Image (spheres, rainbow, N blue to C red):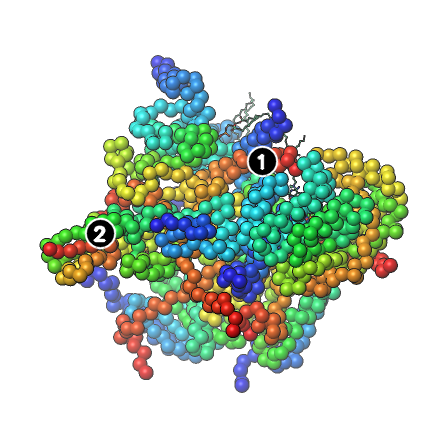
Amino acid sequence: TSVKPIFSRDLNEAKRRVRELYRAWYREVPNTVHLMQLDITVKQGRDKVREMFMKNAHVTDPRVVDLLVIKGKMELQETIKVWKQRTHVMRFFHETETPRPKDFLSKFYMGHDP
Amino acid sequence: KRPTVRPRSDVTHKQLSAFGEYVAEILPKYVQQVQVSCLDELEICIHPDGVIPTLTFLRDHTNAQFKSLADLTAVDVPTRQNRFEIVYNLLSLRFNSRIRVKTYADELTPIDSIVSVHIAANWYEREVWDMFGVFFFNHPDLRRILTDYGFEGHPFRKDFPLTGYVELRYDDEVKRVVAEPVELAQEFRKFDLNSPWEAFPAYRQPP
Amino acid sequence: GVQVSPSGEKITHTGQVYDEKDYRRVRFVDRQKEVNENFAIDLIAQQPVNEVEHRIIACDGGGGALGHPKVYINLDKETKTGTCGYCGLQFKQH
Amino acid sequence: MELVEVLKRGVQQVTGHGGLRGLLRVFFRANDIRIGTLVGEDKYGNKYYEDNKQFFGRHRWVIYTTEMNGKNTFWDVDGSMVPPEWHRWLHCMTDDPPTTNPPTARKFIWTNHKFNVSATPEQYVPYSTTRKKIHEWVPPSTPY
Amino acid sequence: TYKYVNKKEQESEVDMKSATDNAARILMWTELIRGLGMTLSYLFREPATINYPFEKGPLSPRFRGEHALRRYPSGEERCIACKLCEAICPAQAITIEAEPRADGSRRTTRYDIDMTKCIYCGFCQEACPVDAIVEGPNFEFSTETHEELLYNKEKLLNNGDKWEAEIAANIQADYLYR
Amino acid sequence: LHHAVIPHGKGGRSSVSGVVATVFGATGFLGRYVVNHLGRMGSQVIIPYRCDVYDIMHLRLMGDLGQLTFLEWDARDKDSIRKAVQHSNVVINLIGREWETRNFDFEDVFVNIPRAIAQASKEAGVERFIHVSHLNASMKSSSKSLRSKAVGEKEVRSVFPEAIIIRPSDIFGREDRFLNHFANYRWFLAVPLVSLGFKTVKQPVYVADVSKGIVNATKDPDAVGKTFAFTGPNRYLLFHLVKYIFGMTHRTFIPYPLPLFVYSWIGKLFGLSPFEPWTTKDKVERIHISDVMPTDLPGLEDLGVQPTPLELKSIEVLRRHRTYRWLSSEIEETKPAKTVNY
Amino acid sequence: SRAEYVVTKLDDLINWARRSSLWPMTFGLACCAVEMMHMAAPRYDMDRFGVVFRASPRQADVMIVAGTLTNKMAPALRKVYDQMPEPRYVVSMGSCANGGGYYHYSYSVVRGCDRIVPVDIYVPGCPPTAEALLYGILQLQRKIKREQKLKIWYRR
Ligand SMILES: CCCCCCCCCCCCCCCCCC(=O)OC[C@H](COP(=O)(O)OCCN)OC(=O)CCCCCCCCCCCCCCCCC
Ligand SMILES: NC(=O)C1=CN([C@@H]2O[C@H](COP(=O)(O)OP(=O)(O)OC[C@H]3O[C@@H](n4cnc5c(N)ncnc54)[C@H](OP(=O)(O)O)[C@@H]3O)[C@@H](O)[C@H]2O)C=CC1
Ligand code: SF4
Ligand code: SF4
Ligand code: SF4
Ligand SMILES: [Zn+2]
């Protein structure tokens, strides 16, 4: 209620930047699969991009979306350059972590947690 | 004469209170709550719209040549809605005195950057962002410094756990250094130590 | 007090010996568990009882600043004997 | 002259370990021929020589045993074999050896020191010194 | 006060003598033969090295290394499970769990020190009001495994039963300073 | 059920599972992945080793404190095996060789050693025993290894029933001897193949799949008298498979036929070696017999693993063999192999 | 005389070589690296024992993890350990690297270098005295002295 903006009048002007960011990531992924010798396909990389976008698709405050664009631009800086490594890039895929069950009964069989 | 306790001055207290009146009456649009501690230290508190004018003033005025930035910090206080109490520690080198400038922030109420005033503040602002999440306008780089590259979180907030949310170890299956969820062989034994007896009645928060 | 159990392991002054079904005996294979032979119960019981003259006395460990904090023991009873808390030295009066 | 005196000192160093057998036994085993005053021997066989004209890192030294507790330490020499009676003197914590200033004897102090054990058996395996905290219900051996 | 390090007073004095001197500083490497002679001087000095396992560096009674739990001359266990050594241990290396000994005495059923968390600071030995745990002299207990450096009550009591002849003497030296 | 083998934790490192396991071929190629998948969820892994301690270092990690216990042993000497299985719930036999030695033959690797281990397991009183035979293991086969492995698969049942016998296909992995073995045929300027690779079918499987399968079978209440066929998907014809190997490893491809007798003699004189041989007669024989259609048996998906295609994990193995000018090449530039069903 | 005896003696010889010429790596992260320097200093000269630093890992036979190992520096440590050519050894120095040390419960610290690289010997301290690290090095020498590699080759 009558708060200040950051880089955004409201949500459409921010979704503009969001789509620009998706654009940069989609153009950047094949270069990172090549530079650092990743052992994946360009398809699943872009799928991970769209997934990590959809993880924040439930939000409406423009300031949150702007800060998320900022964080994504930082990650894109680190990934365009090779400051980070195959380790940090493959850290998104969760290639070792066993899948956390989403069923009641398996949780009941292992653990007291919901 | 009391050897165990610290000796107190008068002239420094009077000097810094007078200079607080000076800054207050000369920069009223931005100033709040000027104060001088028991130990001789001045402390000015500022509306975030006043960061650049106040810092440029204290850097470039003749009676206030605060042209060396010592620190730029932040203090997470979840009680107050504007959590982060951002601080600037400055010295003069012409009058041999220090001053403190303070302003507030939130996760979604950033502050103007200061590199146009002190170039020292580049990495300090990057650190405040890395640690607390306070975005800074018109900053050149503004990326992390201290944390890992693929790091999710702002550690020095009070709402972040000390042991973190992820943990590392090398797996032979993938031949990498994978990040795994935190799982300790020994839980950190938190201790409750605050005695239930008022030691300092001067700071007695009344009801 | 270094009696063994039917499994064959040594037992500590804290009765601790792993059960026959406990898998945590593997760590003592081609190896050994460190267990101390000099027990404190037996060695403080292998001490005399210090007759004294007064009814209240004072026990430091014996070295002053090297013992324990100076406490005082009452010796009015005759059903039993006084006993220090830090050390286990016993006392009596006649 | 001076050269002659230092060569005489060298000859004294060469001919002060028994014979060639002992000279080599010391030289190939410590890489030093330096002679000192025998301060005192150990119950295992260490020697603990001394020579105060040297500077303050070589005026005390050990010549270790060839067998401590069945290990054949002719070559596998290590610093843990110095018992605490001589640790204090060798590391220059005192100017008082245990020949003149021996330590207080106690019924619980180890009589036979042990070298460092980290790879062999006789080493330290950790474990919980506590006991079963929660006790499980032992059901009956009968039906109904 | 202050003073300059690389400030000449001023210039404008030159003669053929000074020019020849500077030109023989140049063209002969004069200021380099000085360093050469320095290193040569060091060649003919007694070196400061020591045959380590035989001759060893000097230490003090205050030196703090391995840990050990002590006893009284009666052989009685000296710790009393007061649990402030773990309260202050700034690395949370010490876990303690206690019970009555069945003699009715306050003693520990547990005393562990993860020696890969201990910063070897001595707060525990200067806080123990009975001088039960100390930080002994030893610094030669490197191991081939992590598990060996996770101590318990038995290893600490063995370190005490081992190094008491040295611990007691170093304490004998070092009290009256604490 | 002892109170210490009760599982606790969120299923990871620094937790407990109750899967105290003796893994006998732990110093190999499948055993390292098995030990990793065990330590990854929290479980004590007794690891008997005969090698030098240099070659147990990579296993020294992959487990929290005290959960990895190594003890030395010898197949000739009993009481070095009872000592290992004395406190265990599970035992996992991965012992095996691709060549005989003066001291140990194939019988004394696949038959007599599992019999001894399973005798010790039954006498100690453990609950399970996971034996690892081969998919082609048959008493009427061509190779000494495969016949010996079928004989061991039978004798293990005869001694220790209530057992689990896993029968994988030829496994591929980072340090295998299947894809690396076919890729090292570049040092010779042409690759020989019996009948040019046709009339031969291969259904390889990945190490992670077999490892997860074993690690679930040691917890599945099923699989007590069940054999398994750890095959993997996408049955392949040998010529096309080697073509895919030599495309992903972008070197070249010069195939040509060769009979089995001269290639057997080649394998023999290559196996004349005191060191680890490059090729052997039994290896050629095992390479040039097809993999059985495994659909008479459960497999992985009856155990809780979705098998991984070769095309997704082969580059991790084969980029080692590439040169510059091709090392920075992706998976999607090799026109994948042609699958068959037959 | 006998093949096994000849093999034992050849093992002794190669172990002596790898034991007497070990070339650690200039890898010092924190305070413990200063005691590593002091072990390179004249009092406890490493070069006396045939122990000289090579800044490259490929010219290095051992690494000394002297300092705190962060989540940000662990990939580099592992890349360097891989780049070292076998036979290769690791020596964890100080409570920060053996375990977590004074930072075990923090968010950017791996709670032991043994989570990332295998460790032959652990040197405890904060910091360890240079005599202590020298004890660790000579313990690594004692360890190499009993490899029996060619013996197991003969007995396979
Ligand atoms: C009869 C009439 C006719 C007679 C004709 C003959 C006339 C006299 C001729 C004299 C000429 C002598 C030649 C000297 C060459 C050196 C020239 C020189 O000026 O030095 C070069 C260099 C200068 O350094 P810089 O401080 O920057 O000064 C330059 C200012 N623009 O300074 C340096 O060189 C420093 C770099 C080199 C350092 C290397 C370390 C060497 C250490 C000394 C080794 C000595 C042992 C030599 C043994 C050799 C025997 C075979
Ligand atoms: N391509 C494959 O790998 C396939 C393998 N299999 C089966 O998988 C199992 C393991 O395969 P893999 O892991 O490749 O085998 P490896 O050769 O990779 O390692 C096997 C283990 O067996 C041990 N070993 C071998 N011979 C002896 C012996 N005589 N005495 C004691 N220990 C011995 C070795 O110990 P050390 O190395 O220390 O001697 C090694 O750790 C085998 O049973 C094999 O039949 C089946 C199909 C495919
Ligand atoms: S010396 Fe310091 S860090 Fe070590 S156990 Fe004692 S109090 Fe803890
Ligand atoms: S060691 Fe000392 S400080 Fe620690 S619990 Fe025992 S008596 Fe208390
Ligand atoms: S263990 Fe101590 S001395 Fe060594 S790096 Fe850590 S804090 Fe520094
Ligand atoms: Zn008392």
Measured as percent of width and height from the top left, residue B159 is found at: 48, 71
Question: Which residue does the numbered mark 2 point to in the structure image?
Answer: C61
In percent of width and height, residue D111 lies at 33, 38
Q: Quadrant of residue A16?
A: bottom right
Q: Secondary structure at mark 1?
A: loop
In the depicted view, which residue is nearer to us: B113 or F273? F273
Rendered image quadrant of residue B1: bottom left
Q: Residue at x 79, y 44 (%)?
A: F143
Q: Is residue E102 above or below residue G35?
A: below
Q: Residues within 10 Å of mark 1 (few under 14, many from 20)?
A: some
Image position of D67 (left or right of A109):
left
- Is residue E59 or residue B81 the one in the foreground? E59
Pointer 1 chain:
G
Q: Nearer the viewer, residue F253 or A83?
A: F253
Q: Does ligand 6 reach within 8 Å of label 2's beta carbon? A: yes
Going by the numbered disc 2, the residue's amino acid type is Gly
On the image, the x and y values in percent for residue B163 come to 48, 63
Asked if marks 1 and 2 fall on the same chain, the answer is no
Q: Is residue D131 left or right of residue E73?
A: right
Horizontal side, residue E33 vs residue B95: left or right: right
Q: Is residue D74 above or below residue C48?
A: above
Q: Specify the amino acid type for callout 1.
A: Gln
Q: From the viewer's perspective, is residue B162 above or below residue D9? A: below
Answer whether residue D106 is visible to the viewer in this image.
yes
Q: Position of residue A113 (x, y in %)?
A: 54, 72
Residue at screen point 22% across, 53% down:
C89
Q: In this rendering, does residue E15 appear at all?
A: no
Residue C93, numbered circle? none
At 48% from the left and 48% from the top, the residue drawn is C28
Q: Name the residue that disc number 1 marks.
A: G148
Q: Is residue C50 left or right of residue B63?
A: left
> Most extreme residue toward the bottom, as rendered?
A1
